[PDB]
Image (tube, coloured by chain):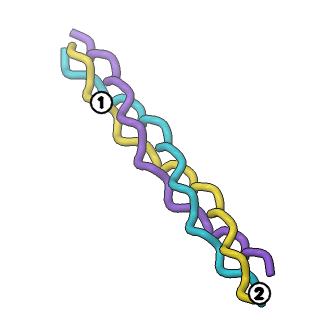
Chain colours: A purple, B cyan, C yellow
Amino acid sequence: GPPGPPGPPGPPGPPGPPGPPGPPGPP
Amino acid sequence: GPPGPPGPPGPPGPPGPPGPPGPPGPP
Amino acid sequence: GPPGPPGPPGPPGPPGPPGPPGPPGPP
């Protein structure tokens, strides 16, 4: 008969990367 | 009928960790 | 026809936010 429907959504992706360095401390 | 097509990609992953601390302030 | 396979793992997440402030400067 006809093809079945598309599969389920895949898994959520991997975490994003570590953020940028923070700002300098005060004098 | 044949097995169906692949499902769609899952969503983007979670945000990455906070970045590292900034450097020491000026003198 | 059986449901197709699951979709692929999703894309990476976004970067984390910038890190905390650096430590106070030296005397």
Identify the secondary structure beneath mark 1.
Answer: loop
Instruction: Please identify the quadrant where the C terminus of chain A is shown.
Output: bottom right
The residue beneath circle 1 is: C6
Q: Nearer the viewer, residue A14 or C5?
A: A14
Q: Given the current orientation, which residue lies at the most extreme front position?
A: C27
Residue nearest the viewer, comparing A22 with B1: A22
Could you say whether the residue bearing mark 2 is in a helix, strand or loop?
Answer: loop
x%, y% of residue B16?
Answer: 51, 53
Q: Amino acid at mark 1?
A: Pro
The answer for which chain carries disc 2 is B
Comparing A10 with C17, the one in front is C17
Locate residue C6, reporting x and y percent: 30, 30
**Which residue is at 41% across, 37% downward?**
A12
- Labels 2, 1: front one: 2
Dividing the picture into quadrants, the one containing residue A7 is top left
The answer to whether mark 2 and mark 1 are in CB contact below 8 A is no
Q: Do badges 2 and 1 share one subunit? A: no
In the image, what residue occupies the spot 50% across and 59% down? A17
**Which chain contains the residue that carries disc 1?**
C
In the image: residue A26, left or right of residue B1: right
Displayed quadrant of residue B21: bottom right
Locate residue B7, reporting x and y percent: 36, 29
**Residue C1 in the image: above or below residue B26:** above
Quadrant in which the N terminus of chain A appears: top left
- Circle 2 sits on which residue? B26
| Quadrant assignment, res B25 | bottom right
Q: Amino acid at mark 2?
A: Pro
Q: For mark 1, does the 10 Å Cα neighbourhood hold few (<14), some (14 to 19), or many (20 or more) residues?
A: some
